[PDB]
Image (cartoon, coloured by chain):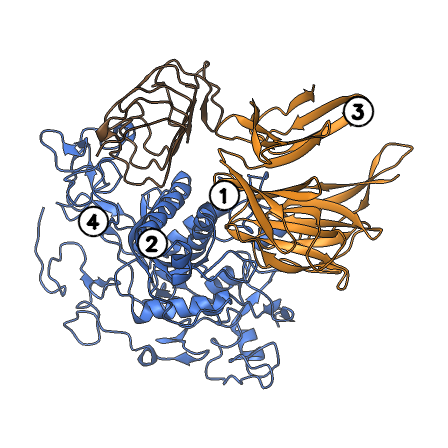
Chain colours: A blue, B orange, C brown
Amino acid sequence: NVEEETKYIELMIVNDHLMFKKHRLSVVHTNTYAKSVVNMADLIYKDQLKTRIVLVAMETWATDNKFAISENPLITLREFMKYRRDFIKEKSDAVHLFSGSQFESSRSGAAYIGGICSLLKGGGVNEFGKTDLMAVTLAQSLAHNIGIISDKRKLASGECKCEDTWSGCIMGDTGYYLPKKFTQCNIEEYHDFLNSGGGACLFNKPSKLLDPPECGNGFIETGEECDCGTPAECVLEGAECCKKCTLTQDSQCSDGLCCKKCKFQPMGTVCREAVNDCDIRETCSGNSSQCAPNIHKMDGYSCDGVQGICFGGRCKTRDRQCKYIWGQKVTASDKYCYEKLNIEGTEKGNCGKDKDTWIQCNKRDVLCGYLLCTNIGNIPRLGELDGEITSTLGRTLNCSGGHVKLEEDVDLGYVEDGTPCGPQMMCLEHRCLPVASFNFSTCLSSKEGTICSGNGVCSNELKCVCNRHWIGSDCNTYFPHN
Amino acid sequence: TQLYVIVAQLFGGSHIYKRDSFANKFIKIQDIEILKIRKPNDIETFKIENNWYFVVADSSKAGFTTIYKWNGNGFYSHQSLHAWYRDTDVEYLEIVRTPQTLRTPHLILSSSSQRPVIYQWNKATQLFTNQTDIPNMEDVYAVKHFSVKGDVYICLTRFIGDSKVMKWGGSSFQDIQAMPSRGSMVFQPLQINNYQYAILGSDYSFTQVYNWDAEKAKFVKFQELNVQAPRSFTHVSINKRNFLFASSFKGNTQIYKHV
Amino acid sequence: KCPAVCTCTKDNALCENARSIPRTVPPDVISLSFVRSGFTEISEGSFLFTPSLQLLLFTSNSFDVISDDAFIGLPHLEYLFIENNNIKSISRHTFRGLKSLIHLSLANNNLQTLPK
């Protein structure tokens, strides 16, 4: 399935001048050092995650640091990410900073949780360290970016623990003696993230790498007509397709799901079933060995008739917010709490985060104020509590809320932006606002007030993907075919 | 006459067991704090000014190196020393500094990719203060000292990088000799039968035995042993016999009677 | 697998003494260790089995004849070490195919000449 498919995370490394000076000002040494670290992290990820981290590019500042460098991991991470947004433009799934400034914190590297495949969130910062040390830090940070984090609630409950009890696991504080195995909850979080639609940009094979043309490296690069890998593992997959980076008499493929038994599969086959309603099934082009590019519902499309919205391919509901923030057993409360707590109250219902004078929420809409769920546990899966978890009690409901934080300034305790409040009514700056606030673009439509001429759904690339037997770009002409 | 053994585990924290001189049973005298002590790497114990202090370092960077009293105290009871950095190994020694006339206690804190730190047991602060750096190189793994004719000679050991045996001189050390590292995660000096030897491990060679040359003042190749993954060396002398234990991380610990 | 004559362990091919080139090396090992080699001819490409290998030692040998492009097939090899190997002469085209090599050592090998 989609999980079993080989993910390809396009990573680019940004390097500051501190470790450049520490490496005797050598460009080539830093380049090969980054290549070795990338290879080591890929070897880590290949055992379980089945994900190859392709070092698409790397930048090292031989001159000096462009922006302010501080020992605070959060401030330095923000500066690196804003520098990436301002200057870095090349397509890359993850943008990771090797921080020469060794952070004065207790955590090795600072990476956003579930932030991969994002312009302002796709990557993290890894501090200076030993080759293995920063390789482990990069592995932890990339696990963070793909939503793989140590589960605090399961740690307290003992639901899942590190099977490498010798020296702990990678997700925890980086001990000197590195382990070799990830926990099963790491992989479970990976399936949950991929099924949610996150990390959809990791399914592309780059054609250009920092590595010279190497036969059997697992990627069809420049100068290689086909690549089935080393013949040791080529027997299982693509045995007759490609041999020694060369075709076997009459052939059309090397690997890939869209090409079964080294031959082209029939047209219309689904090489990737949609994970949810936010995902769009991918069909092979009929002449491309690799599966179709990942396409999801455009940002603003609802998971259901009214409730829920797909952002970046990930569904968002109040119930989904409670599940991500608090836990699976925790579900969003009814409108009763929303209209009985957000209207007036301290620490119970608040629109904006103001400890002194809490922001009042109007009765027109109360679905963007304090996030209220049902049966909130002792501790959330991720984040921290700003004080104590708020608890509030003809129908009786167990009403609860909190102020779950994160490594970013954004507060997960409130309702995340874009959560629906009604018809085209979704959160923006802790308030229900229409689509005009977000200024969502209109896809290729021919009628009035429709999407892709009514029948058809626009993908994430703002391009229409018409339905069956609709070859027109704007879903206007019918072309029967067999 | 009450043994307080420090039983430290990478999981579940550490404990201090008390061995009764009568029942010979090890009862946990002090459950040491586990909030900072999670993955211990090395513990160094010493007594000074009739105060028993032991140094704790965590293989994880979160757990900071700290010195604790024999009974057992909290996070930073009397001093903090090295924190927010790497904590790998610590070694206690006694060297004569330039300012102080008498013998002055010190600690050496070696850390991965971090400069080793000298710590003077300053009596004015009564703490292991004066965090400084040796002028030799970066990323030294292990450290241990000894005294040859009053002059202190100490080991600055790296796993692959050429390790050093270097002489103390009052403010910093003065270089004496350098020897190759071929898988020596440890290099421990010893004094057996009044003979100054030193053992460098070899994860990727035959472990090497140096004897202090009484004439060249340099550690010449004395002998070559073969031990599975050496990690530490510890010597005993009972009656008229001497024995040495060579630890083994990936196999059986070796034992050699010094004859 | 793990040769009996060698002292190979779980995580290494710790060969104490090999009569000649061991071609029976599995991809399980991550490093090599040769000491007091008896054969005098450095063979050619005898580790065309695992490019992921990184380390090997040559200690106190007599490799009077050494293959050009010696031990080819290790582009990822970076720990190239020869010590005490008393060698009459070295083939000119011996150091090729090693594009990711960081550390070298030619110790106590008693060479009087080196080619261009």
Secondary structure of the residue carrying tag 4 is loop
- Amino acid type of the residue tagged 1 in the rendering: Gln
Mark 1: give few (<14), some (14-19) or many (20+) Cα within 10 Å. some
Side (left or right) of B15 relative to C55: right
Q: Which is more N-terminal, label 1 or label 4? A: 1
Residue ID for mark 1: A184
Q: Are marks 2 and 3 on the same chain?
A: no
Q: Residue at x 41, y 25 (%)?
A: C84
Residue ID for mark 2: A26
Give the label, 4 or 3, closer to the camera. Answer: 3
Mark 2: give few (<14), some (14-19) or many (20+) Cα within 10 Å. few
- Amino acid type of the residue tagged 3 in the rendering: Ile
Q: Chain of mark 2?
A: A
Q: Are marks 2 and 3 in contact (CB under 8 Å)?
A: no
Cα–Cα span, label 2 and label 3: 55 Å
Residue B238, label in figure: 3
In the picture, the quarter occupied by the C terminus of chain B is top right
Residue A207, label in figure: 4
Q: Are marks 2 and 4 in contact (CB under 8 Å)?
A: no
